[PDB]
Amino acid sequence: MNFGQAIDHLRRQKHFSVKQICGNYLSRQTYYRFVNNEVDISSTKLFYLLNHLNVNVDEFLFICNNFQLEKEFTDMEKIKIYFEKNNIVGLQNLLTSYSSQINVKEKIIYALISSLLGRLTNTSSCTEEKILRDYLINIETWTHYETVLFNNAMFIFDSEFIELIFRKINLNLEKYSTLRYYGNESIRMFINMIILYIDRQDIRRAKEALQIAKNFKINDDCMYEKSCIVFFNEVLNLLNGEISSLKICKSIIKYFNLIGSLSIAAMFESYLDTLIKNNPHITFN
Amino acid sequence: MNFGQAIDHLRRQKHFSVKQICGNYLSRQTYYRFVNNEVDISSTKLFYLLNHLNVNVDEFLFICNNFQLEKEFTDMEKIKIYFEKNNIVGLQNLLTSYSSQINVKEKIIYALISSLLGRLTNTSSCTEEKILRDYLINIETWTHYETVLFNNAMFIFDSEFIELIFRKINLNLEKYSTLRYYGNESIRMFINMIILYIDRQDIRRAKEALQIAKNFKINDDCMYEKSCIVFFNEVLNLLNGEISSLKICKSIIKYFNLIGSLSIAAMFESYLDTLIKNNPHITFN
Image (cartoon, rainbow over all chains, first blue to last red; front, side, top):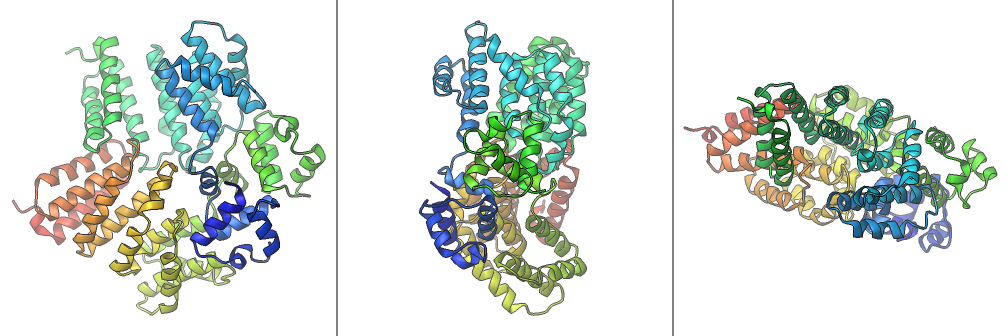
């Protein structure tokens, strides 16, 4: 649905007048033609209109795309799942649709799908891993896109590279602490790094990664994140030998189950069972 | 900082080329003058540029405003605090800055500050409560703005009005369930309603409000919200007589304390102490 329709739909749903929203920045003729998709409007005049509608741009865009997040971000979660479940078919299908590679955006995801398919078919995707590596290593302002991309690409990279990326994003990651669903998505990626380091028996960089995640300024309502911080800290303690930390891991699992986070309680249940299995000294007496 | 500078700062921080971002939709001369704030650009061409920067508009705007949420939303949290703490001075100061009332936005917050000052000085603000009531009652697309406004205005309104608003927003509130920090802010307002109904000894509409909040589709990572749902449900059970529900309320408090949500654990601690004090039958044996 084009911007003209969405603005007018929001204007009528909030019982506003064209004058109330257009003020003395836009004409009725200018406003009408915009509604019918005859004319575009300067960006400062769109934000003016949204400002007077009392509507945020992210809310706006999420209506213009028929109540759906943007295709790149939704394709990125599909990619995540298809690789988890060894779904070569979904991966191969997403590879076809991005094979166009019209812009940088289509090259990164192309390279991401090829590189994950390479891992599933034990084939070289030397070119495509290089595209990904070069894009990520030259990010000095790290946004949501790179965070989504990095949660998804992380495990194809050697630990020196992951450490490089982690050390090099601390700063900006902090700046948007006040950002909604971004500050929190930054933390979740740090947990993914800790998980991946713990899983690679590279405990030394997991300790350094967690201590950084603790120093991140975390609002007391960010309870999934604060839970992850605590859980994984006790999991590090366990690996340094303390069965006192196993009760704390179990109690965090019980509390997920108490509040009906049953699917997440089971993921942590499976992880702590998988952790005791691979390092049996944790539980020893 | 104007849009031109922000785009170019993001472009250089991500080591992109003017051609990579401008593609064949914008000229170098057009792009440069935009950077120097000589020319604006059509809204579809700004979103094009942000799309190629791999940056979301909300992220973008949060950089253009020097890493700060928009003044209206930050003024709204200040208003919340100043009313909690009986700070007539901050309220009176915010009233001065909006006394301009240039647009709808400045009229709503003006009316909100006057109405909260009226409650603190036991004076009539009959005109201003009417402005607020009329704005809220005619919202068929309920956005974040109205949610922030309503958390803040809620308690000046009779319970029939609050029920009216609650029944009338279920639908749209659901649509943006997938929305980040919005779906979740919708739930928190529902808890505020439940709190306010429980506090007005109007248990009957608290039961109806909670049952609706339970039917809301809540992702398992939304743990502060799922915790609130569970806590307040057991608090309703308590009020219908079951000391079995008091252990569950205490365990949810203990888990906030375990994960370092110490300020939120104390708020719930104080509330359950204040709840037992006003309805002593809860604990009875």
